[PDB]
Image (cartoon, rainbow, N blue to C red; front, side):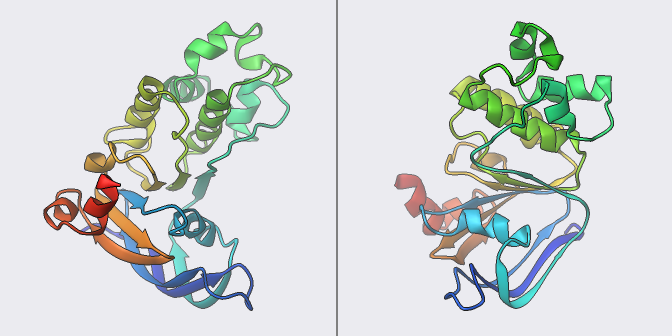
Length: 227
């Protein structure tokens, strides 16, 4: 097995110390460099799991350790009023070859070609929801982080663009192939591509295994697939 990257240790989280826990005694370590899929019904706490890893919740009990720099792509993206390149860079030092690669892998090169000033076009110009979401992911990919928390960033994108983005940045061999990716995803076509799958039920872990492990076993993942 691979290096321990993220360790979650007897960890219970809530929105405030006084609020009842929203995440119940998480006990899980994510190996380094793996694509882990977080899945479950709506309200199962998948979103809050990423927020807990960002330190945004009050930890009632337990310990959390993450190895390396952490990038985050929210579910609802939003861009600062700026040129395209300075949204992807976001204070990162500009690398024209690497920036082109990222905008490519995030399926943004047609669109920036379309713009009047290209990558220097201020937004400024109105952007679709898919464009903001891909620009958001590009910003995290550009950071060259070691851990990526992805809160279903490719949900609203249309299938081929969503395929384009997932294949090129998130999946096997993508731009983030050496990184540890925690991917919350309502979409279940990518699950054969993940190394590990985590299933959540009411803020707790119900199942964990590979795709066909959790398929042979007809339980929480298979119940969710037929839903």
